[PDB]
Length: 128
Ligand code: NA
Ligand code: NA
Ligand SMILES: [Pt+2]
Ligand SMILES: [Pt+2]
Ligand SMILES: [Pt+2]
Image (tube, rainbow, N blue to C red; front, side, top):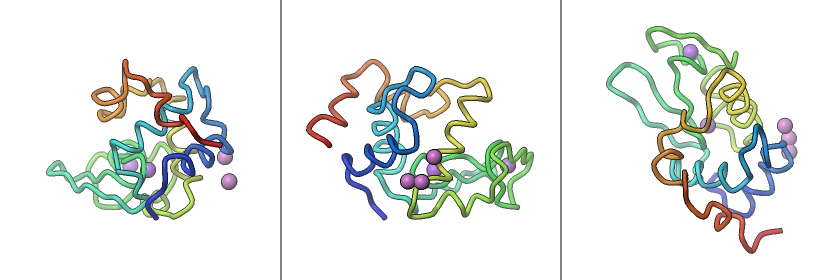
């Protein structure tokens, strides 16, 4: 599924991301836009043997298990295929685990580079 910005905002907000650990909703929407272009099925297979999965491009070394990545920690306790679902719940829950495990949103490179310090509210502006 490829989400709209406002549909993704509403789905994220139902799952508690607005103001999660002091990161407003727009931050989360902005991160998804620049990680995956709102596509739940996005994958990026890396040269280090790891893969980035789903709408938030969560990586298979530390966070989810794809069975083929060296160094697997599986800290979200999920198969990476769960992060390719058309509903976002597993991705959102894993993203909250990532922040709970001592990370800011800096853990997402596209957040750092494309959202940090910008008018992130644009990504929710005009939405119900
Ligand atoms: Na994801
Ligand atoms: Na892992
Ligand atoms: Pt829901
Ligand atoms: Pt939830
Ligand atoms: Pt839900």
